[PDB]
Amino acid sequence: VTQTMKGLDIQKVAGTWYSLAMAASDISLLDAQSAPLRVYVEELKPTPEGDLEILLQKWENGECAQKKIIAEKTKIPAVFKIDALNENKVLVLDTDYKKYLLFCMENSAEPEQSLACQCLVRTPEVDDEALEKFDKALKALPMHIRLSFNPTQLEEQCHI
Amino acid sequence: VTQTMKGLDIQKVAGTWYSLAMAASDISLLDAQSAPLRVYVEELKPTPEGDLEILLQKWENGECAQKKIIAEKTKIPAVFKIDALNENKVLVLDTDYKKYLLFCMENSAEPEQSLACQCLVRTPEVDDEALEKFDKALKALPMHIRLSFNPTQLEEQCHI
Ligand SMILES: [Zn+2]
Ligand SMILES: [Zn+2]
Ligand SMILES: [Zn+2]
Ligand SMILES: [Zn+2]
């Protein structure tokens, strides 16, 4: 179902990011700040080997904890293997490198109950064009919850 | 901003309904089952005087409570006055009476922070055409959360 980006240069996604919008196939995955896949991406750090370190924050033990996820390169381009969040795959759908990035996470064992997708942006501002790209990519996908954040929320993102 | 239905026959909306989809301007209004405006419409009972009794269920005191809301007719058609859920207005946007109904609730004091909208259906089944009408009506509105329920969830709707 999912169509991944072709000709992705992973080195060009490095730097600071913000989670502008999130979507998921199951409401329980994103509803409430303490939900399993409610994650806020803060930085993408690609490696020389072609892997992707994802820095993000997540609600745990009563507060916003900082997590580092190592996404390993696989034989399929724009698809990375992870062992976190009960997910095993990160899929980069699209990016223009300097404004927005669209990606999804899933578990290959049950991809319909585990699919979460995000729209990332470089600056803590609403990019209507990025949201349009996000919505278009989501049309084919069976999403039952969609969240969209404003500039004020994008500053600290996760907060007690 | 909101455009209400013209030529609404309120008597024809009587009977059983299900909340298929919900949307709101603020995430806090709908995120989590215990959220202030997470409400599940079960029945619409119009009166001979032209008022609308809304039967719905809402999470309160650890369980799904049953609520009856009286929507009073106002001088503007398809717009009803209420005194519940911290809202004071019910706006009927569109309906075909026998399959779907779209409505919004708001507080006139702060309509941007209080707007919640729903897509109702007669039967506990996903109507892709009703969702299309819902999405089109929402385009102009500043929604930051969207929820969509499946047939299994639509049977009991709210549940412990
Ligand atoms: Zn590696
Ligand atoms: Zn589905
Ligand atoms: Zn009356
Ligand atoms: Zn807004």
Image: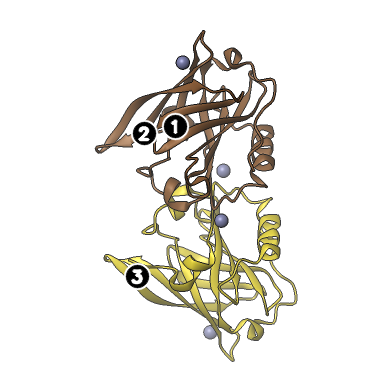
Chain colours: A brown, B yellow
Q: Are marks 3 and 2 on the same chain?
A: no
Q: Report if the CB atoms under discs 3 and 1 are less than 8 Å apart.
A: no
Which residue is drawn at the image coordinates 55% and 76% (left, top)? Answer: B17
Chain identity of mark 3: B
Disc on res. A40 = 1
The C terminus of chain A lies in which quarter of the figure? top left
Q: Does residue B86 appear left or right of residue B132 in this picture? A: left
Chain identity of mark 1: A
Q: Nearer the viewer, residue B58 or A135?
A: A135
Which residue is drawn at the image coordinates 47% and 40% (left, top)? Answer: A107
Read off the residue under disc 3: B64
Measured as percent of width and height from the top left, residue B142 is found at 60, 48
Disc with the residue nearer the chain's start (2 vs 1): 1
* Mark 3 neighbour density, 10 Å: few (under 14) some (14–19) many (20 or more): some
Q: Residue furthest top?
A: A48
Residue B116 in sight from this viewpoint: no
Measured as percent of width and height from the top left, residue B88 is found at 50, 66
Question: Between marks 3 and 1, how big is the CA–CA gap?
Answer: 31 Å
Which residue is drawn at the image coordinates 65% and 61% (left, top)? Answer: B131
SS at circle 2:
strand
Question: Between marks 3 and 2, how big is the CA–CA gap?
Answer: 29 Å
Q: Report if the CB atoms under discs 3 and 2 are less than 8 Å apart.
A: no
Q: Residue furthest front?
A: A75
The image quadrant of residue B129 is bottom right
Q: Report if the CB atoms under discs 2 and 1 are less than 8 Å apart.
A: yes
> Which amino acid, mark 1?
Tyr
Read off the residue under disc 2: A58
> Which amino acid, mark 2?
Lys
Q: Nearer the viewer, residue B124 or B77?
A: B124
